[PDB]
Image: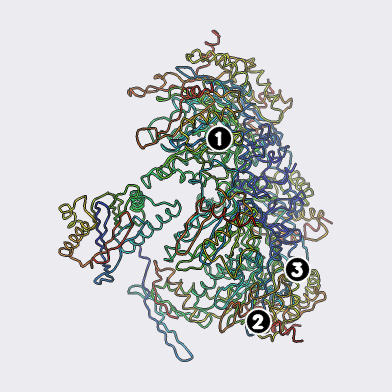
Amino acid sequence: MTDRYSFSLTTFSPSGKLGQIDYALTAVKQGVTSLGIKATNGVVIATEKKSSSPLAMSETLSKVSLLTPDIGAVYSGMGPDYRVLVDKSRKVAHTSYKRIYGEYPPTKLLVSEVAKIMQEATQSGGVRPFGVSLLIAGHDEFNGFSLYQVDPSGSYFPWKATAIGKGSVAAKTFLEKRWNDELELEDAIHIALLTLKESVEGEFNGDTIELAIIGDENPDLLGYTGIPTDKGPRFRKLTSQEINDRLEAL
Amino acid sequence: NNYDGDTVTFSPTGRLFQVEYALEAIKQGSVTVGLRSNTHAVLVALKRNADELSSYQKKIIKCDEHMGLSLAGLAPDARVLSNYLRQQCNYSSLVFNRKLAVERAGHLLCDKAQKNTQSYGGRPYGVGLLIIGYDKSGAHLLEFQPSGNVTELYGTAIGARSQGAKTYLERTLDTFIKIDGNPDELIKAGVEAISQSLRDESLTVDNLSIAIVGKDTPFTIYDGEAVAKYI
Amino acid sequence: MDIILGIRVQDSVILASSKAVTRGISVLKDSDDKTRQLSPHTLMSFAGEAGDTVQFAEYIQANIQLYSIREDYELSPQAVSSFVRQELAKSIRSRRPYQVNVLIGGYDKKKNKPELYQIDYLGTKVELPYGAHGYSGFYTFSLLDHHYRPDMTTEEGLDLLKLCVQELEKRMPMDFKGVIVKIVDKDGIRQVDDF
Amino acid sequence: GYDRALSIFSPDGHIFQVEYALEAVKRGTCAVGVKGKNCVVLGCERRSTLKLQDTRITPSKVSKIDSHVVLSFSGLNADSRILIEKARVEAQSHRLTLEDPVTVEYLTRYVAGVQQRYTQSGGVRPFGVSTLIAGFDPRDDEPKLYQTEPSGIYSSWSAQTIGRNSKTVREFLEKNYDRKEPPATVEECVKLTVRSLLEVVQTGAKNIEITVVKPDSDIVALSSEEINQYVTQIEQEKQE
Amino acid sequence: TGYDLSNSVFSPDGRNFQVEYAVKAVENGTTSIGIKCNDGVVFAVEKLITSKLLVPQKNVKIQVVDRHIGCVYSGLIPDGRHLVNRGREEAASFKKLYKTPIPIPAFADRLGQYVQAHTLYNSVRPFGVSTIFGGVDKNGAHLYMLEPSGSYWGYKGAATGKGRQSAKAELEKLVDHHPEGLSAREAVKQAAKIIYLAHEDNKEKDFELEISWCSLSETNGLHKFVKGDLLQEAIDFAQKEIN
Amino acid sequence: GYDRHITIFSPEGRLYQVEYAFKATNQTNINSLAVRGKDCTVVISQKKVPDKLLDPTTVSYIFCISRTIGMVVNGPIPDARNAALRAKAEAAEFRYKYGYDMPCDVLAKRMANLSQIYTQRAYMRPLGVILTFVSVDEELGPSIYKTDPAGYYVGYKATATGPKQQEITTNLENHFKKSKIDHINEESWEKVVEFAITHMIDALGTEFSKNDLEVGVATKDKFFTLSAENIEERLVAIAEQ
Amino acid sequence: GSRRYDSRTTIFSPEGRLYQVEYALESISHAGTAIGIMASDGIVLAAERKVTSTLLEQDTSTEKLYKLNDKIAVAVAGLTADAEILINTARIHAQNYLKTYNEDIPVEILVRRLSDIKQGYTQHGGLRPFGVSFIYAGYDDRYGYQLYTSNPSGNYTGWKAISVGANTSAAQTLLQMDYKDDMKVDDAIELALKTLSKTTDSSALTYDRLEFATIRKGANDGEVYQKIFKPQEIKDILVKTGIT
Amino acid sequence: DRGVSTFSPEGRLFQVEYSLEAIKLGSTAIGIATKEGVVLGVEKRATSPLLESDSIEKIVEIDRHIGCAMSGLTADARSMIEHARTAAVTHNLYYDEDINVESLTQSVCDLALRFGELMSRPFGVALLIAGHDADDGYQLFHAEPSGTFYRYNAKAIGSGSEGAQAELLNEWHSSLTLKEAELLVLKILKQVMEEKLDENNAQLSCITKQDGFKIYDNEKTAELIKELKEKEAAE
Amino acid sequence: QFNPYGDNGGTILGIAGEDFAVLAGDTRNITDYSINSRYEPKVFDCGDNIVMSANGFAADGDALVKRFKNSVKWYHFDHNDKKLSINSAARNIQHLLYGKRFFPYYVHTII
């Protein structure tokens, strides 16, 4: 018994390609489209909630996840792989940062730690790479707002705006026409909804769309008062009702 | 064919070829015989040399004062398995002041050989053993196969052309089982038994190996001029 | 063990180290050299627990020599002293700590300057114009506070050192059988045979 | 832990991973050792497809294991650093416990033992390196030259070469080296070494390294000009 | 293909061919059975007499676990001993921690999980045995049969080996003809009849019969081998029925 | 093509071993169904005992994981029990560590996470099972959460699993289209059980005796399975209407 | 067992080459070019970003050029994720040396240890090698300015000017042509940018597809300064040499 | 590929069998046992004339009363010798006595099968172990990578073995003098060797109760070579 | 605090002649001021004509004799039934004792 697979399952082919990483990106291509847009005073990350059955309660399945009060994640590719990556990501923001410095990590560094975890699934013994591309949006005092893409390889790139998954090629082109460096958060949400409609086929409402923002501090979502320096999470998930309000003035 | 790479693989008809291939090494081995009465148990072994300049590979090993065995196949594997038996016999003596029952000795060997047939990286033991002993329930003879199968018998033989001696003992069963209180006669029967497995070669003085254990006889081995009596 | 002294002057570091090895009511040796050469321009003296001293000294010596052979280069006295401090600082929380007190006298060839470091078993490092370990300090520090000048010649240093040995031979309870004096300068390490 | 037996016997009785490790040696740059009456000289080829090199900082081909022994090699460069490091650590450990520096034979026996260990350990491949180890035993003036190879075998040589085209230079040394009369001086020994490399090298410019070890830790590396003088002198005697 | 070359690999069907191959090893083995009764269980097995040289009564195949459970198996005999050795370790640790002797369903899952574990990795081989086992606990009698896959169920009657179908047919008749229940002493006899009837599928070599039982009234809830007068009585009953 | 033997990606980004483990799911040829009432969550599953020698009381694919959580399995019984023992242990540890009973959805997530690991780690095969967890959560109320060999999991209004799952699924979809609500608007669990059997009968097109079925019922503070006579009592009630 | 699926990453070809190292180098040859040039008064690092998208955030980005300590930096060609693993090891190693000896780590010592780690992945453990080639640019008071390169084999060498990644063959020829020893930093900056411009697989070299850095003694007296160029500074230096 | 400890269909271990082929490529080593002593001789076989032949070390001391010769992958023998020496000395430390030659040989053979998936492969070298003890007198043992050892009155191993062994079958008798054995080893080595035998490419050694194990000088063996050539010409 | 040692009293005596040797010991076994046994033998025949006594703390005495007896057994198994000479027995017993140098067998040993 015991894990006898102590050797790499991802190895270089004569042409130079890393087969499993390529194939993982192929899985990400098949995945449902998700996107991220960076405004001046916030970031929006969105995706379609592909329901597996109408008897399923798609609210119980969250594609957009809070990592820290100021960082949120969304993905394209394999759900289960994403879910465990979120668990691991949330923990590493504590163990390797909060438990040391008494504050939450800046986006680029949390992103860096997730990319490490995904890199190791590319080199370590007896594991396949993760079959997901992440879009991580967040805020921190000294870098402001930022948006990152983490690929199966472990590579991460900062974006003004981008999409990943099914209809990413068309969505990116759409985002290039509409993005400028003066976009306000509400203008970014409006473009996010427009861009998503192109890649969504069936119902397009607040129950089939999942969308969150990194913006102002939300003191009402803090759960307590009395500490002036603690002002609340900048990560917020838009409600099904809040989406439909914006779909009328679309 | 495609299913003989290792012991951990079953063939489509439910065979373990590595275990069968281990069994084959025994078949190439030099013939050894085992038989018993109600008072004594006797091993007889034909020893094999490399050429006329070499010694004759010893086939019989003592385990305790009341137990021992003979081997046919890979001799280093017999050394491992005997050494294990020596410890097991020894443990029983030191901890319980008890002589290890020849039956338990069989069960222990079975379970040691078995583990090497179910795991990756290992191989089956490539040797067959004939264990004789005298314990609280009298004289015994066991046959060990590296498949794990241990079998208690009145008489038997393993090795090349063992079928001759095994047939002979099957015919002689009613005679030799009642050779009680007579060591030299029980040996004679075993020496005649092994003579049914000889081809072109006959039993010489540095060729024949005999062991005996019983009621008033510690497990002792006879080589050289001490077996001349029986040729 | 017992008495180890060090004086840094204008152009050199001079180390004096007692020659006695006493165990119980017997002086077993009166010519013991309580020093190791770590590199061509670095010397370390040592005093403390029996066995521990020479074992630590030679362990350090092997490491510095290994470094030398790897990089084809001599570590600075500052660098060596920091390596030695860290080893002792590790040691003090071990299951059995090295009970060794060292002085390191070196000549930095890049700086063309003598340097003297005092490090105790805890790993307490200090650069000093003059140094002492054990009870010796109680007589020599005040003496050197008075007579020492920073611009002294090697010869003046040796006369200043004679004054220290003399005081110790007058007021110290034990016979330490004199000292072995060694000089560290631009030309390396050499021993004064008549002291 | 990674356990795979990578070095195993083939039906004909060869250990292919050891034998392929020899091919890596055969690909490496030529190295030659020649011992005189009172010295050993290590010569090394340096390939010239690499211009724009910085020769101050680039790893030298001949390494000092201690102040009295040197090691040159042929094969995988990265591999050789692991052997050199271990050798240098053993050198200091020997001085510590025996209170005497290593003999050249001992240091070589250690290096070869390491190499051999990598031929029947699980989860490792053999070293793609053969070494020339040269020097003088403590308080001894007799020159010592040894050679090791991936299998783990080592032996003493009056003169030996390893690397690419080593068979050509070995040929040269086999007819140009007299066992009855080894190169009586440093100059003679360096020249015979430089000559043997010139059979294989190309230009005697920045292609040849020469290191001279003499008794009592007397090791020095020759500069370009010093070596170039040997190159110049040899060619003028050749036109005859 | 090549799906059958490695344990724990799913075929496109969703099958583990290596287990199915282990089942072939079981089908090759001698016949063993288990009959559940009023207040207990009865086990019996066919012992092929390969040669005259085998000592009768002296190559015992039925095994006890703890003091209240009995185990018998068909296939690779060593593999069965391994499973019992574990069974004993499991039972001992249960009795150590919880004091009470291990209940049969609890004991059944211990063996089940252990055997199931040998279908999870490619570095182990599945067990080459089907094992019939059971006993009496605080909730009465239980009989089980466990297969190489790790699958096991509770049984009224159970059979495995070369004569499993013959034996199964014979078991089903008993279940139909005795809805109220079979007595322990009756079941011992029936076991002897069935082993003799299942021997038809292995009739080259003649055989030796071995029977054991656990009964709340007859053996006081403890596992005991059927020997002497009771055994010869059961043999005779069986002999009468084949003629 | 060793990419089909272990859980690494194929050129098209697929995991065949995970896919084949899904096919192992239907190897038992049993269909299961879960629905929710106001106060309860009812799960039912077919019970096929082919062999006359089997003890029918020991043939079960419904498990009591904790006092509050029940789990029905679709797939081979060895893998099914493997899952059930781990679930029990996980639910027991959660309670000891965190001071309160493990929720159905959290246990589901945890088991799904374990399943995910087998899809990423090579030495461990996936279990050829689909696990349906049921309870009446003290916070979320009646709950159905379901796990598969891919490591996927999601909550349900109702659900079905097995070879003829699509027929049952649409049958349930069509009912909830009609009723316009997320659950069975019924007071007693007895009638929710009756609804479950009624709608299984219609979708499968078969009639059931008391021994053709298996029923688990989760209520507040306990999950229990029904006896043959409890089911028979329920079958009589359906027939008399 | 699992033997079946073992690639055997750390074995020799019949020709005495390491398959995986060779294939990793083949992978690196498709990564964006990076150039290092050593002048007498400093070092230039120049690297081409891999085909950029217009919506990439260019200023808060780092892909090619990383800082190991205040005196040493690296240019990266290959898998970035692999490179960061190694960069973090290198960064910790530098600090260890400083904590031990109270002196900044000599460049070669750092380069050797990082190269040694790579070597290990080619000899034992059964893991794939790091698909990375580094250009090390740094300063210490022993050798002054130094360029090095290491590759997946764990072999490292010292250079006056060197390129890694794509089109090294053409790039090296060009560097060999116009490099001379008495060169200054500003001349080297030009040579670097000119070479990339001629070897690039893009249509035209622009500020958004480059990373740039210098290591000068151009601070104030006997001390070294690392300058990782901002986007606008690359835009200006590209105009100053008349490429755009 | 396939497991390192795999059986062939003929019941033999592949890797052990293949290592026996490696030994057949080795240089010839011959041992003859007499009542006056055991002689061990080997062919040095220098790969090139520049190689200093006296650095070729294929005859080795294990203890004062035990010596050893080798053939095959000789680099594999170093750890076997290291073990043998430690086994010998250790036994003297534990029991204040010399260790029996057979006990030594059994100890070395215990390493042999300690390979698999312990070391990665069997040894690729065969050993001739020659010694003396008070119980069984002068002994010669052939130790194989199989883990098997046979006692021999005489034995050749290596490339020239089957031819040399056939010669040893004719020449050996129970009354050979030490001198007779010395000459016989030289004679048979000369026969199977490629290059012409002399004091530089062949080596002799012996173990006697009185003087223990001794490797002969090149001067001593040269005279035995000369004595041999003169004796063959003398009839 | 638990004291792992005790004193079982008694005394032993060994004398050697030209072709013989005697090893004597009283048979009394005690703890404190009580008698445990009037006849408890502590002189033993260990095979190969070696007699041995380990006197002091009987539990350590018995443990040592038990180990040495077992040593004699294995000596035979490992060295072709060779007789263990008294000088070799002595050297073996030294290692048996010194092996517990930092938790000693509390006995005077005579063979």
Residue position for label 3: B159
Residue E231 x %, y %: 72, 61
Q: Nearer the viewer, residue A14 or H174?
A: A14
Amino acid type assigned to the residue bearing label 3 in the image: Gly
The crowding category of the residue bearing disc 3, from other C-alpha atoms within 10 Å (few below 14, some 14 to 19, many at least 20), is: many
Residue F219 x %, y %: 54, 28
Residue I13 x %, y %: 40, 84
Amino acid type assigned to the residue bearing label 2 in the image: Leu
Question: In the picture shown, does residue G127 fall above or below H119?
Answer: above
Residue position for label 2: H224
Q: Secondary structure at mark 3?
A: loop
Q: Which mark is residue G175?
A: 1
Residue B197, picture quadrant: bottom right
Q: Residue furthest bottom?
A: I18
Q: Residue furthest right?
A: E243
The crowding category of the residue bearing disc 2, from other C-alpha atoms within 10 Å (few below 14, some 14 to 19, many at least 20), is: some
Q: Which mark is residue F154?
A: none
Q: Is residue I29 visible?
A: yes
Amino acid type assigned to the residue bearing label 1 in the image: Leu
Q: For the point 32% across and 23% down, which residue is it?
A: A226
Pinpoint the chain carrying mark 2: H
